[PDB]
Amino acid sequence: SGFRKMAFPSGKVEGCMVQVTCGTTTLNGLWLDDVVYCPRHVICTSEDMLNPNYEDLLIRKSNHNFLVQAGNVQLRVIGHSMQNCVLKLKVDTANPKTPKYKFVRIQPGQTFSVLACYNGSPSGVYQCAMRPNFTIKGSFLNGSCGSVGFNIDYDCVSFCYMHHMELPTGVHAGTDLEGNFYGPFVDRQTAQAAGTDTTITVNVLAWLYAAVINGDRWFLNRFTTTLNDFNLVAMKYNYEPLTQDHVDILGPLSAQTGIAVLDMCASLKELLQNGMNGRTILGSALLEDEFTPFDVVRQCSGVTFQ
Amino acid sequence: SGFRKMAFPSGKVEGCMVQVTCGTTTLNGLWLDDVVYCPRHVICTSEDMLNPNYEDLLIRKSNHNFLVQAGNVQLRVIGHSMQNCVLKLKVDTANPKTPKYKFVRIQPGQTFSVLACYNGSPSGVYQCAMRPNFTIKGSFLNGSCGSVGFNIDYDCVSFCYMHHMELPTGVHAGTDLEGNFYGPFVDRQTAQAAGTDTTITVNVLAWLYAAVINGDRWFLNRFTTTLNDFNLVAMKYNYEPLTQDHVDILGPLSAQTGIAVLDMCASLKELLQNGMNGRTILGSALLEDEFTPFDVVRQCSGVTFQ
Image (cartoon, rainbow over all chains, first blue to last red; front, side, top):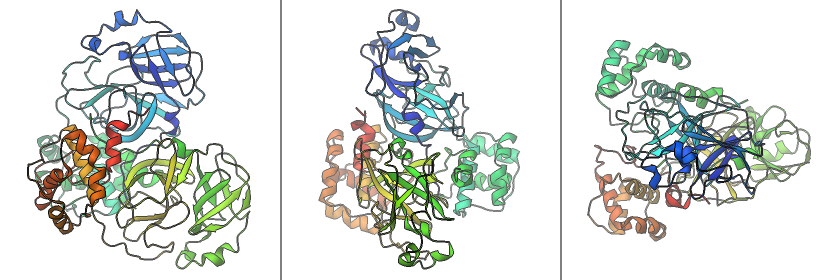
């Protein structure tokens, strides 16, 4: 019956994108209630991006030096201000297509959908993970700053990401929706380091369960092993250690399939020490870590949706 | 700046899904104007699916034996009828969220987005290819029949697929929107054959161009070769032959990157005869054929969207 990397429907979010402009720079903004969210470097030129003094740069604009635009319609300004690395504009219309929504600060290894936008218009949507080094491997061209990430919650859009930076190494960086960067980075054109990205072990395991459920099941073997024994090897291959909170949330798949977490680890242990590069699981010739246990459970069951 | 498998925004389509029911069976339907589209086997039980006489089964229902439902709201019936393997219900409301749209019959190797739905509600969206054997490798659980595929066109939704069948081999089958199956299949629970799925050669090539543009560029080499020379090998590895229409549409990428189609073929020729299984391109440890040349051109350029 199959297993696809899929994203959440993006309807609820498309009606919230707008374009923000501040005499020259245009990027994307998130229009909820009577408030537009957007990255604060929209008040910078390209020169200014070497070292922005955001204090001094913002103190010069004003509630008209900012060009918000939702559909036909310009909107009008009423209040501006900076919440960490986001600006929060005030404007003269509560947004009717505003949905039930939260903001939250997700953690490394959780997944979400990105709605890539250009000049306030949607381009596409894809499902990505937040790397353990708090970057994402996204797909963004210039102008896409302000595109948002959203996981879901359940009928209630949980905004988790705003895109700000492409690093000079190729990877992508951004904030949560009240402006707090994920990871060390700053909004400043500099060669800054992420360093070591690890493979998300709990996600690889959930994906192995998804494989068994469909029946790419060749990779299994009856070795057993301990946490301790498995976590030793995982550190050799830069896989995240797997603690007891991970074993627990895999329990549901443990039960539906008949396979203890620690037995699945053993077959993965061995996929790692060799890489039986004969074959394929769910097609992929590499081990997948962008599905969480919750994702597999939805793509299997809990989403024959209402 | 990166390269993701991404789907089109699904906003325009979500507002067109409804649930169709005919005393028991519920599947998904496409509600445009004052017409609902849905698979015709919604008038079958599970027993009946062995050998349905659609003639005789339809002649028994009627414009009330059918339970359409869009949001709150039931709708009312007015006319029913069967267009090949789809039913086209009449009902008492033109659908306001109906968008500009066409139907067309796409060809093997073209790509589109699927909006997987359950009981008329959206579950997710993903970007898949139509295999040369006119199947798709989708992700569908029971109830998802009537989920639609749509490529786009340009601001105008082009509906290209309706899901009908999971084959007893795992792959998926369906029709265009005026009811014509893609491939040989019939809407009838039987062990029926697709046979040989080939790799879509023009798509692999466009993906190799996408790789160079980002700069996973190791796989290139200065062998040259002829069409003839390349197509000989491709048939050894069940890759589709590549004719002159394919060389042409690759021309745009040929130009932006500095690499003739036939030179790129040569590096692929050799990826094929060995599989330099050392490495990775765009991450993938296998050759990708679910991006078309148009997709790469959009994911690179023509979609800094308006």
